[PDB]
Image (tube, rainbow, N blue to C red; front, side, top):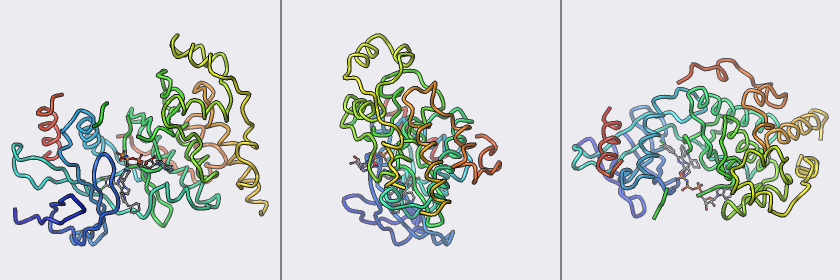
Length: 333
Ligand SMILES: CCCn1c(C2CCNCC2)nc(-c2ccc(Cl)c(Cl)c2)c1-c1ccnc(NC2CCCCC2)n1
Ligand SMILES: Nc1ncnc2c1ncn2[C@@H]1O[C@H](COP(=O)(O)OP(=O)(O)NP(=O)(O)O)[C@@H](O)[C@H]1O
């Protein structure tokens, strides 16, 4: 196919449409390799993600298929939007790779976490994550795995969530809600805990709960926030309830102690620091029955200054062989 050309990207070969030029590797993960490129047709820089045989197993396949479908069943500036999708392969028999194209972003939220932000930028980023999550919820999509490596930003402070969230692979749990860690039921505000973890990390410049596994994760949570109420214990399955109730007890630390003044000059900034800590205290709540909702977070004074109805109330959205065919059909449309 004359429309495509191949480029060497590390150990991988990127076979892309000739419109994408000066391919440069910008990162990789378990799912695929990402390049920056110049799109000569749009006269814009783009990010190109290659999915190598996404149908290779149930985990890669479910994710690739669910993401391809959801990216069409979603329309919001704080959620990933595709510019293009293609395969260099001509037939289902030859089908191997899927290439996804979107606007090139400047940095991920990890990089943003490593810097000091003022309250306008910090509140604007959090407002955008909430707008993004609210849009997902309105379509019945509850993320459950928001993390800063899957959130990208531009120099103008605009933000996008790259994925749609939630089993053997031949993964980052730090932002997962207690009700996800403990196999409890969950509602929309499961995503509010992850936003709290991210916000807390934006302020501390350190992962709040850096667990090597779910056991370690649960200990780091209780060591800082304290042992949850008996009413929370009442919602756990007997086995999880016995394990959680037999863990070493902790009174927990107060939010001024957790996020000291040292982490936050002018009167404006003093008031905003007070409001940021109040919002952190409402999101970083173990019990989802007592944790603030996405709607109430958007009405919080720290966030409310950015409130725009057009952004908050935007119009709402197998075997290896079967997955191969389902993914191929989605790519071909
Ligand atoms: C590669 C850096 C960030 N990124 C990732 C990561 C996410 C965490 N796991 C590893 C990959 N996926 C995409 C991405 C996700 C979905 C699609 Cl469809 C496309 Cl094409 C790209 C982008 C990205 C997206 C846009 N711009 C950028 N820009 C980089 C530039 C260098 C600094 C980090 C951000 N990365
Ligand atoms: N906020 C963080 N601070 C520091 N290190 C982190 C943080 N989050 C994740 N990491 C590390 O960054 C590395 C990449 O993590 P991650 O982006 O979650 O994986 P991934 O394969 O790129 N995800 P995906 O694209 O969804 O398949 C791992 O070594 C993590 O332990």
